[PDB]
Length: 277
Length: 277
Ligand SMILES: *Cc1c(COP(=O)(O)O)cnc(C)c1O
Ligand SMILES: *Cc1c(COP(=O)(O)O)cnc(C)c1O
Image 1 (tube, each protein chain N blue to C red):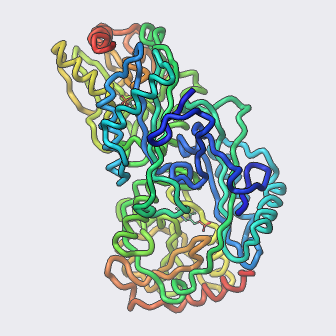
Image 2 (image 1 turned 120 degrees about the vertical axis):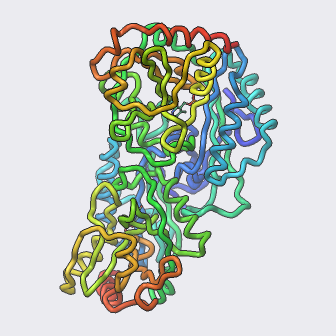
Image 3 (image 1 turned 30 degrees about the horizontal axis):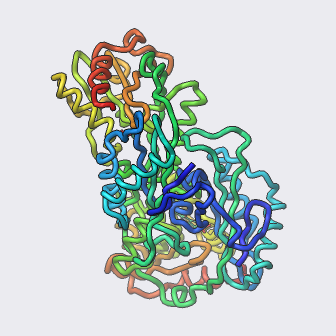
């Protein structure tokens, strides 16, 4: 299909990454994933905003305005005739002779972006999934959506080997997030989730789900919960741009409550469904 | 110039990295840097061994024997007529459609290697450098020389901005290592350096310096020291394939002893010299 290469939409074949692109040698870059439903981009602005925020935290300066970027993403979805799926895009510090310190301000960041046709995970949304506790060994700057995802691939891989869908990370007892999702816990009608600090990424879906909770008048407490507490919850679920509201009905062979999708998860899913095109 | 691409040496212009190379999207890979002196590859075997160890730690299987790899690096040095500089080579899990977990056991890892003429840091070895303490916020698997280097890029850049040579990282007072070097201290004729565990990277130059100390009968104590104990040390220096034994005469405006390169650092350099081609 077509790829966004900086400010140009070109055939996939024409794209060539330099061996000295700082993203390829240092993972010196940031990314975003945007869900597309029936040809319409979902919360594009929230995501573009975060891309620039991520880039700013590590001092990268995107050469285009949010509007141009918005235009490019819109044109990318048109060229590829994307119906239902997602868009992936990243920005790196640019191609420059290997060195740790930041290059010269002459170096222009490299923007790559492509689309992928991918249906909604219906069975999962409906039936729920198995998860597994995996120790959080990532760096202390999880608030940046960077390309340094080695700790996350290892965790997701451990989960996959154990036949689980996601890995619920924890920095010594305290639950933080999934290898690629935010974690929610419902107990006695109340929604709990780790507060957005440096120990987790403030998910867009996480924020939309907290919004939905306010609309249906469900009390939200942004307080950390331990691994033991997580197992004693009534309902449990993870969120991400592609997973949406995915129920977690089991953790390490232990059924959450009774192993069925809870009442409030269902309610929150229904409220979320209204914000979709 | 010329570049090692898998098991071939080609013109730089012939190499093309895919956008979906896991080293570009996850920093999912490992690398090494070998110093070349007058056409001869210094401690090339120790470095080849570590590349394989590192790759094994994250379950990447390099398709060639270390023997075949040694050969290729040898042809790369000749093809580029490299006299004194270094070789940079890395291995990534390979190109596969984006996903966190490992691809099918059919995706061949991508290997890239190149050279660069770069003289020895004579002035630094002779006069010493200025450094600055920086909090270590890197992940917990520092024994792996992986491509996830955003934490070291930020620290080195901080050191650079403060007008310093290197950043000496520390996890709550305990000095671990540099952003791209190992740290050693000397107090009362005894050599101190942090133990080789998951907190630091067991450098080759570090091991050679330990051997030099044994050869010259200097006692070695592999125990951690604090940022305070570091400032009270008689001598200080950092090591790396490209820095060799670079003395540190000042940390954040605080002089080490009297701000001059010391006795034992000189002895160690002299001994290390007897190993250079
Ligand atoms: C991307 C990501 C998420 C989900 O954020 P969304 O914007 O909701 O997709 C959650 N956790 C981590 C660690 C992530 O990298
Ligand atoms: C590469 C590296 C070193 C030095 O290793 P050498 O084999 O001596 O070059 C030291 N510290 C870190 C953090 C490194 O990445």
